View 1: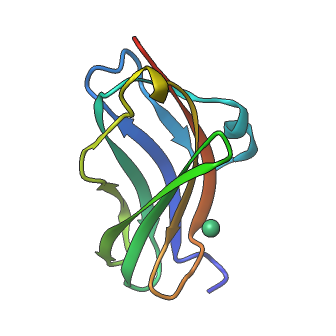
View 2: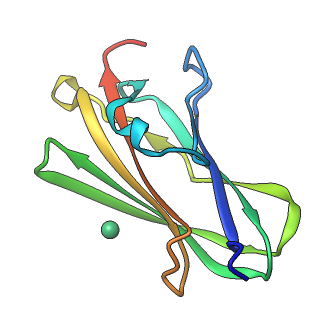
Amino acid sequence: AMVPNVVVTGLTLVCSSAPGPLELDLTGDLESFKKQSFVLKEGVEYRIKISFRVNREIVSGMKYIQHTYRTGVTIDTTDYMVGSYGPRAEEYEFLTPVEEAPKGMLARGSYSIKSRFTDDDKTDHLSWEWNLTIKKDW
Ligand SMILES: [Li+]
């Protein structure tokens, strides 16, 4: 040890009607994501895919927690059970159940997202922040 047990390397929004790839490289500087955004068409169904390595010892109780913030005054949190993953060379990919982008004129515009990849022991495997913008059209 010192070497980290879990290395989170990517986030991908999985949506077949998105015209281009929607991906964050989580291995580098994380600050630049704060002023970027992914556009999603209102009401579209998508999933979030987290890519990650496990290095040393099995990790069980893994969990993906996402807080969604809207205009600094409204918050919604979802916590997803990820599973138990043995150490191994090859990357893993977790995908959430299907979610639906916010729908309605009043639901358009910007949302901030606080993502945390953690476990039963509250290890901060990676925390990060990114943004969605909900639009009428792609
Ligand atoms: Li938090």
